[PDB]
Image (tube, rainbow, N blue to C red; front, top):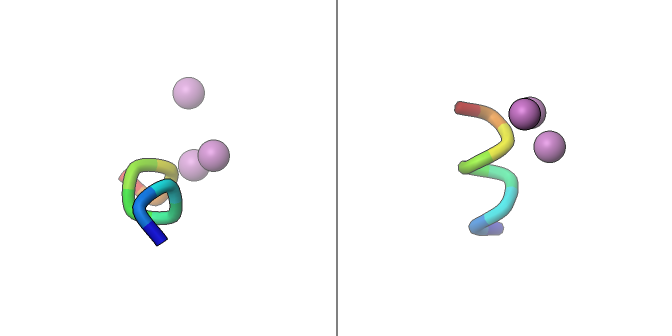
Length: 9
Ligand SMILES: [Hg+2]
Ligand SMILES: [Hg+2]
Ligand SMILES: [Hg+2]
């Protein structure tokens, strides 16, 4: 989950 946020942005 965390990585998805960082990747997204
Ligand atoms: Hg990305
Ligand atoms: Hg990524
Ligand atoms: Hg990058």
